[PDB]
Image (cartoon, rainbow over all chains, first blue to last red):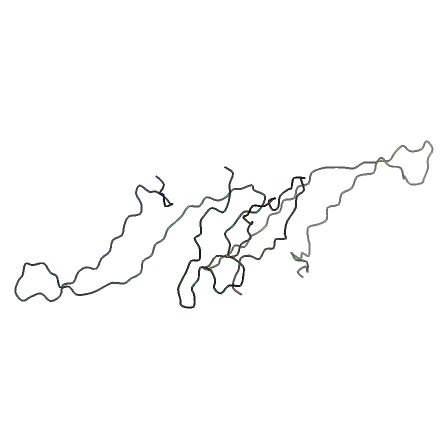
Length: 106
Length: 106
Protein backbone atom coordinates (compact mmCIF):
# COMPACT_ATOMS: atom_id res chain seq x y z
CA UNK A 1 0.00 0.00 0.00
CA UNK A 2 2.43 2.62 -1.27
CA UNK A 3 0.65 5.48 -3.06
CA UNK A 4 1.07 5.43 -6.81
CA UNK A 5 1.79 9.16 -6.95
CA UNK A 6 4.65 8.57 -4.51
CA UNK A 7 5.01 9.08 -0.80
CA UNK A 8 4.02 7.32 2.40
CA UNK A 9 0.83 5.31 2.62
CA UNK A 10 -0.62 5.70 6.10
CA UNK A 11 -3.55 3.82 7.59
CA UNK A 12 -4.07 6.73 10.01
CA UNK A 13 -2.71 9.72 8.09
CA UNK A 14 -2.55 13.25 9.49
CA UNK A 15 -6.20 14.17 10.02
CA UNK A 16 -8.01 16.89 8.15
CA UNK A 17 -8.23 20.25 9.90
CA UNK A 18 -11.51 21.89 8.91
CA UNK A 19 -12.20 25.56 9.49
CA UNK A 20 -15.07 27.89 8.73
CA UNK A 21 -16.39 31.30 9.70
CA UNK A 22 -19.31 31.13 12.09
CA UNK A 23 -22.30 32.73 10.31
CA UNK A 24 -23.39 36.11 11.67
CA UNK A 25 -27.02 36.84 10.73
CA UNK A 26 -28.07 40.25 9.51
CA UNK A 27 -30.97 42.21 10.97
CA UNK A 28 -33.92 39.86 11.64
CA UNK A 29 -37.51 40.92 10.96
CA UNK A 30 -39.62 42.52 13.67
CA UNK A 31 -42.14 39.66 13.50
CA UNK A 32 -41.12 36.03 13.92
CA UNK A 33 -40.53 33.90 10.83
CA UNK A 34 -39.73 30.20 10.94
CA UNK A 35 -38.07 30.35 7.53
CA UNK A 36 -34.37 29.72 8.02
CA UNK A 37 -32.04 32.70 7.86
CA UNK A 38 -30.68 33.59 4.44
CA UNK A 39 -29.36 37.12 5.11
CA UNK A 40 -25.91 37.07 6.69
CA UNK A 41 -23.26 39.64 7.49
CA UNK A 42 -20.55 39.20 4.86
CA UNK A 43 -17.20 38.41 6.43
CA UNK A 44 -13.95 36.52 6.03
CA UNK A 45 -11.07 35.64 8.32
CA UNK A 46 -7.29 35.75 8.18
CA UNK A 47 -4.59 34.32 10.35
CA UNK A 48 -1.35 32.43 10.70
CA UNK A 49 -0.82 28.67 10.52
CA UNK A 50 2.26 26.80 11.73
CA UNK A 51 3.17 23.21 10.87
CA UNK A 52 6.20 21.52 12.44
CA UNK A 53 7.26 18.06 11.24
CA UNK A 54 10.01 15.95 12.76
CA UNK A 55 11.53 13.58 10.18
CA UNK A 56 13.79 10.62 10.87
CA UNK A 57 16.81 10.32 8.59
CA UNK A 58 18.64 7.22 7.39
CA UNK A 59 22.25 8.18 6.75
CA UNK A 60 24.39 6.82 3.95
CA UNK A 61 27.03 4.28 5.00
CA UNK A 62 28.64 3.86 1.60
CA UNK A 63 32.09 2.46 0.86
CA UNK A 64 32.04 3.79 -2.71
CA UNK A 65 35.37 5.24 -3.80
CA UNK A 66 34.50 7.60 -6.65
CA UNK A 67 32.40 10.72 -5.98
CA UNK A 68 28.62 10.48 -6.04
CA UNK A 69 26.13 12.31 -8.22
CA UNK A 70 24.69 15.25 -6.30
CA UNK A 71 21.94 17.72 -6.98
CA UNK A 72 23.66 21.03 -7.64
CA UNK A 73 22.91 24.55 -8.74
CA UNK A 74 24.31 25.47 -12.12
CA UNK A 75 27.25 27.87 -11.93
CA UNK A 76 26.79 30.31 -14.81
CA UNK A 77 25.76 33.87 -15.45
CA UNK A 78 21.98 33.76 -15.59
CA UNK A 79 19.34 36.46 -15.69
CA UNK A 80 17.74 34.96 -12.57
CA UNK A 81 18.68 32.66 -9.71
CA UNK A 82 16.86 29.34 -9.56
CA UNK A 83 14.19 28.94 -6.87
CA UNK A 84 13.92 32.68 -6.25
CA UNK A 85 11.63 35.59 -7.04
CA UNK A 86 11.78 37.64 -10.22
CA UNK A 87 11.63 41.43 -10.53
CA UNK A 88 7.82 41.19 -10.24
CA UNK A 89 7.97 39.27 -6.97
CA UNK A 90 6.81 35.90 -8.33
CA UNK A 91 8.40 32.83 -6.78
CA UNK A 92 9.08 30.10 -9.33
CA UNK A 93 10.54 26.60 -9.21
CA UNK A 94 12.51 25.92 -12.42
CA UNK A 95 12.51 22.12 -12.26
CA UNK A 96 11.20 19.22 -10.18
CA UNK A 97 13.83 17.76 -7.86
CA UNK A 98 13.71 14.09 -6.92
CA UNK A 99 15.54 12.28 -4.15
CA UNK A 100 17.62 9.53 -5.77
CA UNK A 101 21.15 10.92 -6.07
CA UNK A 102 23.23 8.82 -3.70
CA UNK A 103 23.67 5.18 -4.65
CA UNK A 104 23.88 1.84 -2.90
CA UNK A 105 24.55 -1.70 -4.13
CA UNK A 106 21.54 -3.76 -5.15
CA UNK B 1 51.95 32.70 8.14
CA UNK B 2 49.65 30.77 5.83
CA UNK B 3 51.58 28.76 3.23
CA UNK B 4 51.41 30.21 -0.26
CA UNK B 5 50.74 26.81 -1.82
CA UNK B 6 47.73 26.48 0.46
CA UNK B 7 47.12 24.63 3.68
CA UNK B 8 47.88 25.06 7.37
CA UNK B 9 51.02 26.81 8.54
CA UNK B 10 52.24 25.12 11.71
CA UNK B 11 55.03 26.28 13.99
CA UNK B 12 55.43 22.68 15.17
CA UNK B 13 54.24 20.63 12.19
CA UNK B 14 54.04 16.84 12.16
CA UNK B 15 57.66 15.74 12.55
CA UNK B 16 59.63 13.90 9.93
CA UNK B 17 59.78 10.12 10.31
CA UNK B 18 63.13 8.92 9.01
CA UNK B 19 63.83 5.29 8.22
CA UNK B 20 66.78 3.38 6.84
CA UNK B 21 68.07 -0.16 6.56
CA UNK B 22 70.83 -0.93 9.03
CA UNK B 23 73.95 -1.79 6.98
CA UNK B 24 74.99 -5.44 7.05
CA UNK B 25 78.69 -5.81 6.16
CA UNK B 26 79.86 -8.54 3.82
CA UNK B 27 82.68 -10.94 4.64
CA UNK B 28 85.55 -9.04 6.33
CA UNK B 29 89.19 -9.82 5.55
CA UNK B 30 91.14 -12.34 7.60
CA UNK B 31 93.62 -9.65 8.68
CA UNK B 32 92.53 -6.43 10.35
CA UNK B 33 92.12 -3.29 8.25
CA UNK B 34 91.27 0.11 9.68
CA UNK B 35 89.84 1.26 6.35
CA UNK B 36 86.10 1.71 6.79
CA UNK B 37 83.84 -0.97 5.38
CA UNK B 38 82.71 -0.50 1.78
CA UNK B 39 81.40 -4.01 1.00
CA UNK B 40 77.86 -4.51 2.25
CA UNK B 41 75.19 -7.16 1.86
CA UNK B 42 72.65 -5.74 -0.59
CA UNK B 43 69.20 -5.55 0.94
CA UNK B 44 65.96 -3.61 1.05
CA UNK B 45 62.92 -3.61 3.30
CA UNK B 46 59.16 -3.61 2.88
CA UNK B 47 56.30 -3.06 5.24
CA UNK B 48 53.02 -1.39 6.06
CA UNK B 49 52.45 2.17 7.25
CA UNK B 50 49.27 3.49 8.87
CA UNK B 51 48.37 7.15 9.34
CA UNK B 52 45.22 8.17 11.22
CA UNK B 53 44.20 11.84 11.34
CA UNK B 54 41.33 13.27 13.34
CA UNK B 55 39.95 16.44 11.74
CA UNK B 56 37.61 18.96 13.32
CA UNK B 57 34.74 20.13 11.12
CA UNK B 58 32.95 23.47 11.04
CA UNK B 59 29.41 22.87 9.85
CA UNK B 60 27.44 25.20 7.63
CA UNK B 61 24.71 27.20 9.37
CA UNK B 62 23.31 28.87 6.27
CA UNK B 63 19.91 30.49 5.87
CA UNK B 64 20.22 30.59 2.08
CA UNK B 65 16.99 29.69 0.31
CA UNK B 66 18.07 28.55 -3.15
CA UNK B 67 20.16 25.38 -3.56
CA UNK B 68 23.93 25.58 -3.27
CA UNK B 69 26.59 24.66 -5.80
CA UNK B 70 27.94 21.20 -5.02
CA UNK B 71 30.77 19.12 -6.39
CA UNK B 72 29.14 16.32 -8.35
CA UNK B 73 30.00 13.45 -10.63
CA UNK B 74 28.85 13.88 -14.19
CA UNK B 75 25.93 11.62 -15.11
CA UNK B 76 26.62 10.43 -18.65
CA UNK B 77 27.73 7.35 -20.50
CA UNK B 78 31.52 7.46 -20.34
CA UNK B 79 34.19 4.95 -21.26
CA UNK B 80 35.56 5.16 -17.71
CA UNK B 81 34.40 6.24 -14.26
CA UNK B 82 36.16 9.24 -12.76
CA UNK B 83 38.64 8.59 -9.95
CA UNK B 84 38.92 4.88 -10.75
CA UNK B 85 41.30 2.44 -12.42
CA UNK B 86 41.38 1.72 -16.13
CA UNK B 87 41.61 -1.67 -17.82
CA UNK B 88 45.39 -1.61 -17.21
CA UNK B 89 45.00 -1.04 -13.48
CA UNK B 90 46.19 2.58 -13.40
CA UNK B 91 44.46 4.87 -10.92
CA UNK B 92 43.91 8.36 -12.31
CA UNK B 93 42.41 11.59 -11.00
CA UNK B 94 40.64 13.43 -13.85
CA UNK B 95 40.59 16.90 -12.29
CA UNK B 96 41.72 18.80 -9.19
CA UNK B 97 38.91 19.32 -6.67
CA UNK B 98 38.92 22.38 -4.43
CA UNK B 99 36.89 23.04 -1.31
CA UNK B 100 34.89 26.23 -1.93
CA UNK B 101 31.40 25.09 -2.96
CA UNK B 102 29.14 26.18 -0.13
CA UNK B 103 28.71 29.92 0.32
CA UNK B 104 28.34 32.37 3.17
CA UNK B 105 27.70 36.12 3.31
CA UNK B 106 30.75 38.37 3.34
